[PDB]
Image 1: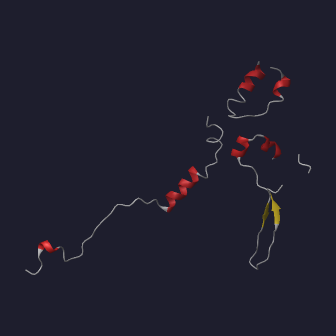
Image 2: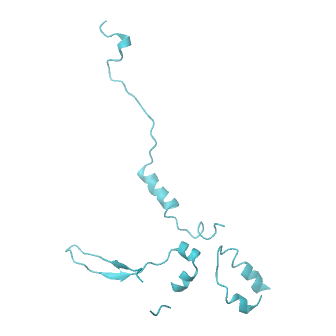
Image 3: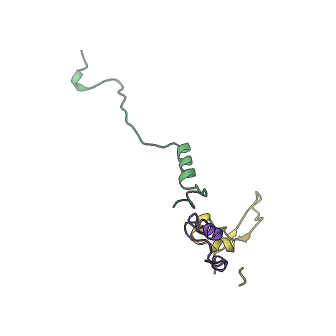
Length: 45
Length: 47
Length: 28
């Protein structure tokens, strides 16, 4: 469990009237190959 | 009596050539099963 | 081995040879 440098993404969505509706930060779920090469990633997930 | 046979054809002559070219549907399938194929096997049962 | 040993290993590279050596040990 994390308690505390930049591997996150800013995710943006706009509607028809050019207005940003989400503008949120997000992090990518690991791929199963990454889990295969590092099983501790499943624990973090 | 005007056209000389050794001068070459005076009509329209249809040349041809074979070409290697995959269709869009075939390429989409290839992406599915060779680059976007993340099935559990082929990942974890590869040994 | 013992139950203490198995509780501190974790999954590893190819996971099918894993989980079957573990099962044979747990059955033993």
